[PDB]
Amino acid sequence: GSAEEDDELFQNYVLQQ
Amino acid sequence: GPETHINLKVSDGSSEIFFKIKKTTPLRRLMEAFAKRQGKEMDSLRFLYDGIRIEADQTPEDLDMEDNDIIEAHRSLPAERNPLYKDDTLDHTPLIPKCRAQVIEFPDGPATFVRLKCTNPESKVPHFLMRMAKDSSISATSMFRSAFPKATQEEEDLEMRWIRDNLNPIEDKRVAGLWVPPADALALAKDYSMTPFINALLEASS
């Protein structure tokens, strides 16, 4: 649910390199 | 006091300078001198006496200053703050279970982060606060972006420069932004009124 989207969201923002 | 002249100390956290001025002299002089001598722009500084901003035309007499009183030179920050952070004193126990640990693959290879999603209660825009599990480094960039909704790129650049010059950041090749150790993160948290959130992030399971 929201947890998975949060996980995907966070990975995306972390790798904003 | 009855003295005609006064010694005043101005501190910006990094450097301290003593000044002797007549108590009838506008503090404009002292503020401009501190900025000049430190190689800083006046617009990047705010000068406070006992928590109150000093106006340029005010004199030590006006303010009833005493010998060896201290003037604090605070850096400028964006004018508006995330209303999530309107109370720096709240206990952080309920925020810890909101944190999440996550493994992220890089080319060499995995690294574990802890994150805390923080939602602006007015705009509903969220930001993540980010911690590296290995050394407990905190992304100061993530803190600043969460703290100041309307920050300009210039303001962000100024702040990241200040962090480099005054605190002890690292660069990780793998992840962008400025990452700082726990003590530095908590110093910034006080500046940004984010203490309960950074406390929670630092204590959370990895």
Image (cartoon, coloured by chain):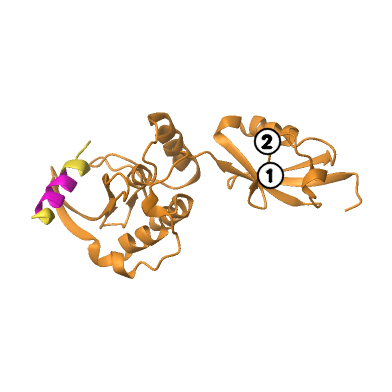
**Residue at (58% x, 45% y) in the render:** B14
Say if the magenta span includes residue A7: yes
Instruction: Tell me which label, 1 or 2, sits earlier in the chain.
Output: 1
The correct choice, above or below, for B38 with respect to B107 in the image is: above
User: In terms of depth relative to the viewer, which is nearer, B198 or B103?
Assistant: B198
Say if the magenta span includes residue B31: no
| Residue B33 figure quarter | top right
Residue on which the image places disc 1: B10
Numbered disc 2: what chain?
B
Residue B119 rendering spot, x and y as whole percentages: 28, 51
The orange-coloured chain is labelled B
Residues drawn in magenta? A4-11
Residue B60 rendering spot, x and y as whole percentages: 79, 44
Amino acid at dot 1:
Val
Residue B34, numbered label: 2
User: In terms of depth relative to the viewer, which is nearer, B136 or B81?
Assistant: B81
Inter-mark Cα distance, 1 to 2: 7 Å
Colour representing chain A: yellow
Does mark 2 fall on the same chain as mark 1?
A: yes
Residue B148, numbered label: none
The secondary structure type at the circle numbered 1 is strand
User: In terms of depth relative to the viewer, which is nearer, B13 or B53?
Assistant: B53
Amino acid at dot 2:
Phe
| Residue B123 figure quarter | top left
**Residue at (20% x, 60% y) in the render:** B100
Looking at this rendering, what residue extends furthest in the front direction?
B122
Instruction: Using residue B88 as the reference point, say whether residue B115 is left or right of it.
Output: left
The correct choice, above or below, for B153 with respect to B146 in the image is: above
Instruction: Using residue B88 as the reference point, say whether residue B72 is left or right of it.
Output: right
Residue B1 rendering spot, x and y as whole percentages: 87, 53
Q: Locate the C terminus of chain B and report the quarter of the image it occupies.
A: bottom left
Numbered disc 1: what chain?
B
